[PDB]
Amino acid sequence: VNLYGPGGPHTALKDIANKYSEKTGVKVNVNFGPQATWFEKAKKDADILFGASDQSALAIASDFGKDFNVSKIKPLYFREAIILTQKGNPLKIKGLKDLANKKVRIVVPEGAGKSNTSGTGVWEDMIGRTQDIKTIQNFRNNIVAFVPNSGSARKLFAQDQADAWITWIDWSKSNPDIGTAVAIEKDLVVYRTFNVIAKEGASKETQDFIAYLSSKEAKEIFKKYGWREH
Amino acid sequence: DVNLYGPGGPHTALKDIANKYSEKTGVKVNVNFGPQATWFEKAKKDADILFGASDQSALAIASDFGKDFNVSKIKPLYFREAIILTQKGNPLKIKGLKDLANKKVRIVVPEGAGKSNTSGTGVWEDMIGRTQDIKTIQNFRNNIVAFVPNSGSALFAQDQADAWITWIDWSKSNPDIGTAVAIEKDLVVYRTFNVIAKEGASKETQDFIAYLSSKEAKEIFKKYGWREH
């Protein structure tokens, strides 16, 4: 069974795929990274596309045309956005409003229309919930880079220069050695989903693996990386 | 002239403001609007200002212009809330997003599916995601019949769908179409109107940008649902 999707969820998926192979003897390959890196191979043998948000999964599945029926995207888990600071949070960042109010350098997970990426719209949806244009302006004025989430990359953009990144909890859980996670205000934070879509006319082994993704053993592994159901 | 380009939506407020500005100052201000593809070529030749209906879409559109615009100069000025638009009279008695997840309803959401730069990308998922319940998220998604850009200056499936996820300014601009239902305060998102002036923008261009923050402009933006606080 061949899976394709963004770096990020791949950490949990590799753990799950390995465990699944132990149990069933069915080979499950987890291919991951920026879409451009695997798009041509996926055109030839993709059984399942996985995604790290709905809007990005929709865009990516829409690039395959007839191979995939975009209405069949299945949300399975969600997780929260976080602030990731330098180790030990030296600036004592307490949330998004604090980021707006301090003289800090922020990186946000935007692709600027050049790629499909899970973070599109996240920073604005959260800071917008302050309903204060000055807060929104101040936060934006502190943004030094608009670049897609690191995903499967262990390096952060501007690692030695920026003070904070807007990213996903599962990135921090997958990379405990990089940065310090700071929780976003509950009244502001957004949650986005992990999803899958099986190709049209998918095999029984493909369907069986999709079902496994909702098994107790899979739920356990997803939870370890910060993915939630309720 | 001062030439503005951007999406349908904010254009109604901007046309009102531009008219008032021209009457006052004698400077001709042209508001060009619609899907990016319909004006992109013209804008490459004479755009003074790009206006936008979200940050992510404004960033994407301004990044299509290369040297002529420095995308770091995008200026957020107002925000407004997402709404639910139902058929006139709200016959299904829709009360919010959770209601849309729970009922048998046909929903249209403002997604571009990576085919265009559009203001609505990520809105529906960010709102219903704040329920923190995967079944609710699944139920809402199962009711979506179309993932298409916000109608803006044009509704998709107007006689077929039961509900649209759209912006308050659309309802204000089109008061005779459908019925607006306010989204749960703990779920709703707010996105911005913004502007960016071209590199080397004229004095007239800069003056018009300033006017968008005048008390006169603020009052017109407010009429169409655009807020500061």
Image (cartoon, coloured by chain):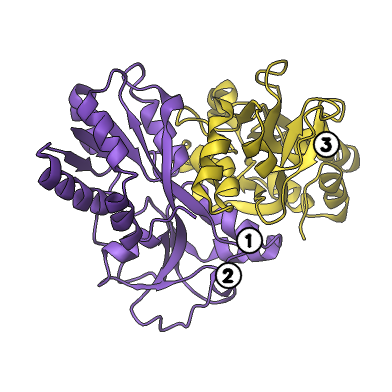
Chain colours: A purple, B yellow
Nearest the viewer among A138 and B211 is: A138
The x, y position of residue B88, in whole percent, is 84, 25
x, y (%) of residue A155?
A: 25, 62
Q: Report crowding for label 3: few under 14, some 14 to 19, many 20 or more residues within 10 A (C-alpha).
A: some
Q: Which callout, 2 or 3, points to the residue nearer the camera?
A: 3
Three-letter amino acid code at the position of disc 3: Lys
Asked whether the residues under the numbered discs 1 and 2 touch, taking CB atoms below 8 Å apart as contact, a structural biologist would say: yes
Q: Mark 1 falls on what kind of element? A: helix
Q: Secondary structure at mark 3?
A: helix
The chain to which mark 1 is attached is A
Name the mark nearer the viewer: 3 or 1. Answer: 3
Q: Quadrant of residue B176?
A: top right
Task: Give me the C-alpha separation between circle 3 and circle 1.
Answer: 23 Å
- Circle 2 residue: A100
Other residues around mark 2 within 10 Å, as few (<14) / some (14–19) / many (≥20): many
For disc 1, the marked residue is: A136
Q: Is residue A42 visible?
A: no
Q: Chain of mark 2?
A: A
Q: Which structural element holds mark 2?
A: helix
